[PDB]
Amino acid sequence: DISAKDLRNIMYDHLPGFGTAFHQLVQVICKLGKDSNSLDIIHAEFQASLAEGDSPQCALIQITKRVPIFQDAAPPVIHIRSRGDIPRACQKSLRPVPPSPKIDRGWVCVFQLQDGKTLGLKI
Ligand SMILES: Cc1ccc(N2C(=O)C(O)=C(C(=O)c3ccccc3)[C@@H]2c2cc(Br)cs2)cc1C(=O)O
């Protein structure tokens, strides 16, 4: 049975660069997937999408649209100390949080900084 660490590694092995917004999306898909016992269907959708010729980036997005735990779901909140805890390759993807962010519309997560600042990571 696939673990969350295993799934993260499989997905990472298909992504170019490191610490990009897509890497963070893998983290969120894996966390939310573990918590909803859905790692197997997520892995299956990921592989099916690649097998059809989709880019791995499109495969990750398709998961947010096809797997029901992500459908019309709010992005998870992740508490951090400062913007420095976010990878360099994510920095330009950080945005002010809109009123009703949804994962399946590209809002991967919401970082909540110690001093109260809040930033959404957008794909
Ligand atoms: C199954 C799983 C997947 C990923 C993680 N994460 C980590 O251990 C971790 O460090 C995660 C991050 O994405 C992260 C990114 C930047 C700064 C801090 C955390 C990341 C998180 C995803 C979400 Br949604 C909340 S934390 C944790 C778990 C877990 O079981 O604790």
Image (cartoon, helix red, strand yellow):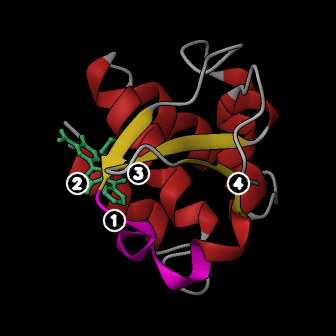
Numbered circle sitting on residue 27: 3
- Residue located 34% across and 15% down the image: 36
Q: Quadrant of residue 103?
A: top right
Q: Is residue 123 left or right of residue 10?
A: right
Pick the front one: 115 or 16: 115
Q: From the image, give the main secondary structure of the stretch colored magenta.
A: helix
Q: Is residue 12 magenta?
A: no
User: Mark 3 or mark 1, which is nearer the start of the sequence?
Assistant: 1
- Residue located 20% across and 43% down the image: 3
Q: Is label 1 in a helix, a strand or a loop?
A: helix
Q: Quadrant of the N terminus?
A: top left
Q: Position of residue 99 (x, y in %)?
A: 76, 22
Q: Amino acid at mark 2?
A: Lys
How far apart, in angstroms, are the residues tagged by discs 1 and 3?
10 Å
Q: Nearer the viewer, mark 1 or mark 3?
A: 3
Q: Nearer the viewer, mark 2 or mark 4?
A: 2
Q: Nearer the viewer, mark 3 or mark 4?
A: 3
Q: Is residue 47 left or right of residue 107?
A: left
- Residue located 48% across and 53% down the image: 26
Q: Is the CB atom of the residue marked by disc 4 within 8 angstroms of ligand 1's nearest atom?
A: no
Q: Is residue 113 visible?
A: yes
* Category of crowding for the residue at label 4, using alpha-carbon neighbours closer than 10 angstroms: few (below 14), some (14–19), many (at least 20): few
Q: Is residue 98 left or right of residue 20?
A: right
Numbered circle sitting on residue 51: 4
Q: Is label 3 in a helix, a strand or a loop?
A: helix
